[PDB]
Amino acid sequence: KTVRLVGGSGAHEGRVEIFHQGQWGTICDDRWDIRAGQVVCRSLGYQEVLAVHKRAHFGQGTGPIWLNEVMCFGRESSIENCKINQWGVLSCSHSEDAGVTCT
Ligand SMILES: [Ca+2]
């Protein structure tokens, strides 16, 4: 599994982290929307997204920020199948790390 949620009350919620080129890294909140939240939640086996969260709601991550320019229509099987302009982000900081709450 290349996606995990960290820092939440339970495993159904947290900061979104994605594993890419040997490293777990985070997602910037700039373009973070409920369609991407649905993709993340369902790829983790949950029926629905309940909320997306910005501004390191579940604490800041460390390490790379892997995604910022990612656009999901909502029915992709994983965030890696959303439209990703590039991997690796220098225009954000971990204070912007994105989060989700699922089912
Ligand atoms: Ca931001």
Image (cartoon, helix red, strand yellow):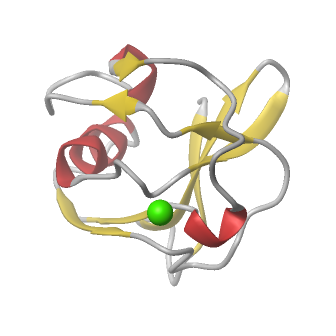
Left/right placement of residue 79 relative to residue 73 reads right
Give the image quarter of residue 52: bottom left
Quarter holding the C terminus is bottom left
Q: Position of residue 85 (x, y in %)?
A: 46, 18
Q: Give the residue displayed 63% in from the left and 53% down from the top.
A: 92
Left/right placement of residue 75 relative to residue 59 reads left
Q: Give the residue displayed 56% in from the left and 78% down from the top.
A: 58
Q: Position of residue 65 (x, y in %)?
A: 69, 44
Q: In this view, does 17 lie above or below 78?
A: below
Left/right placement of residue 48 relative to residue 71 reads left
Q: Give the residue displayed 14% in from the left and 28% down from the top.
A: 73
Seen as rendered, the residue at the extreme front is 91
Q: Position of residue 79 (x, y in %)?
A: 40, 29
Q: 6 or 61: nearer the eye?
A: 61
Q: Give the residue displayed 50% in from the left and 76% down from the top.
A: 10
Quarter holding the N terminus is top right
Left/right placement of residue 11 relative to residue 23 reads left
Q: In this view, does 74 lie above or below 9?
A: above
Give the image quarter of residue 59: bottom right
Q: Where is residue 51 in the image (x, y as percent from the top left)?
A: 24, 69
